Length: 252
DNA sequence: TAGTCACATCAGTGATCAGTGGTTCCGGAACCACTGATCACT
Image (tube, rainbow, N blue to C red; front, side, top):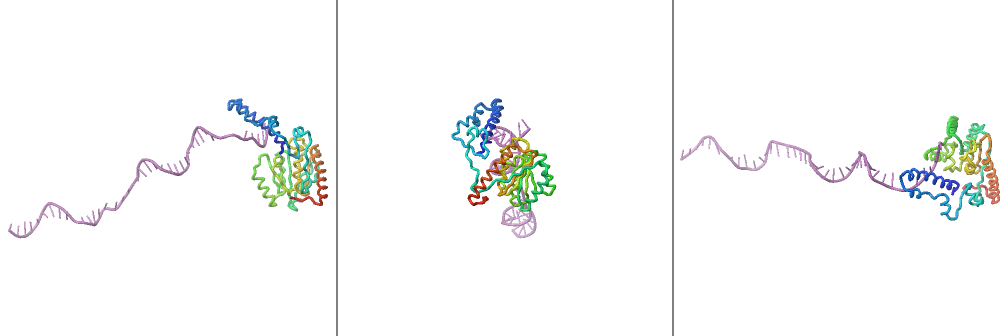
């Protein structure tokens, strides 16, 4: 599962650990048998394994190369939930719209998410939002568990609505109550903001019954809009399946 | 320039106990009664 990062993790771990076995064995700490007591080189693992099945809505490049590009689809949940409605606007008009949607969601006391790129601008923007009397928090590189766990307590107690993270937010958050997310400066072509990143944000925003995505960037990256288009067409497919069942998207 | 990486222990290091070395300390005037003269008499 998540072999798209497990296999790169395998090679990266082997490389870093063999760099350590250098300066360990190469520099008189253990014998080369230490170097042997290692993660299997990716090829060695690929041999020692049996039949291989990768599990991810975003198959890895080398994974697709191994599998020939074919796969097995499972995207329509039996529940009937559908993907969010995406919107794209330029970077300008971001603070005003952000506050407006903050208040609109606070009418019903709903959640919201925000992404960012640079730490300085991220925390500056969160500071301004706090200055405008906004129930907002932010995340940085090395935040610790207590902060976001008390954030979970707060959100399930209806204290705040929005959060402002950069990268690590992408992992370890399941928020059914957010019907709107904002994606800052997706225009830049970055590894951490790749098609996998946009698909992850799409899945995040798909949690709510009528979730919504809002990416604010001057230009539109190929990955972001192709991901949005495939998301919306599979969303139409899911809606068709729902209405064929005579069942509205069912929260579960 | 960067998040994950995971294959225990000599040797301090002394606390701290928890055993050993040593502590230490009172009341003494009473109590039991016993014991060398002193006139007495001879």
